[PDB]
Length: 131
Length: 285
Ligand SMILES: O=C1N[C@H](c2ccccc2)CO1
Ligand SMILES: [Mg+2]
Ligand SMILES: [Zn+2]
Ligand SMILES: [Zn+2]
Ligand SMILES: [Zn+2]
Ligand SMILES: [Zn+2]
Image (tube, rainbow over all chains, first blue to last red):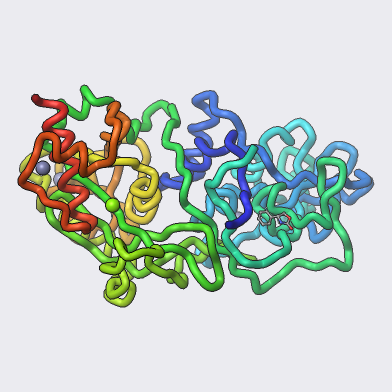
């Protein structure tokens, strides 16, 4: 009974971060040791004529981004572990995340390392025009 | 090709909305087209779901610099025979709102300790994963009728994991700087470890120079077996699966070839005792 959610390619990294005290550090160290990025993310078929904002209610990918389902880009949702923010709730689950095409191979790692500009809503270093 | 790790065990006949699905596989079929997913304005997210996620299927074969391996070789386990603790878990099955996974019920150790836990699972919700009590039934059969009373005599996991750390500390403070859990068909024991074990780089005790064997969530601190009072997690434990040593039959039949002083009382701690006994006889004779 039940429906499989994962593929065998993710078993090692998911089990490693599922047991870690600091899962974010464990994932970054896993990548640094030559480990493969988490795969089986929710990649969207979209027009690519969107605003380009980082976290949206609908896919807003532009010609330089790929749109993904938010929960699938969150290490804490992927491992089924506690979220690090004090309220314990997710900011990616329930939304779509726009990831630059050059970083689309590792969406979970991209969201773990980068921040969204509170002014323009674009990723810092990847679309934020502000100073 | 799929795995049973993180298998969705809910009874809901539909999948998840693309924004709430942890994976492409779990996205509802309505949204799937040409290997990808589409957003359908007018088909909204679900804000009330509770989906039990299975913790059966972990694979601890990571190779990360600075992170010790949990599963050790037979020769390394022999060197740390003082740290050996037999471990076995008798589980219950998920029922009513979920089906398809086993939850830890009675945790047994070669120390003779048996701890009964409240059937608890990892339930995904629209906001996070809720570690909470779930409906469960003892396994179908008469060799498991001793578990029926235990369904109501369990302790919450915050209490159970404190008792495990206290028991291991009292047993191992004068014997070893480690714990080596000695297992037979490790699958369910490794699943159960997710409930009371944490891993990371090697650390030292906050009160001394001995290696850290315990962790506290409350204070974000590490402790050896001598200073772990109040600690809730087993930190960086080691383990080995005796079943994988080329034995042809079941635990009891292999244990009984060398030992006649441990009669099977059909309880978690009895299996744990038999496992450590079999490991000693196999490794040192
Ligand atoms: O309708 C469905 N059911 C499948 C599924 C897979 C995993 C978890 C939940 C649901 C995908 O589409
Ligand atoms: Mg057993
Ligand atoms: Zn999340
Ligand atoms: Zn900006
Ligand atoms: Zn100490
Ligand atoms: Zn024996």
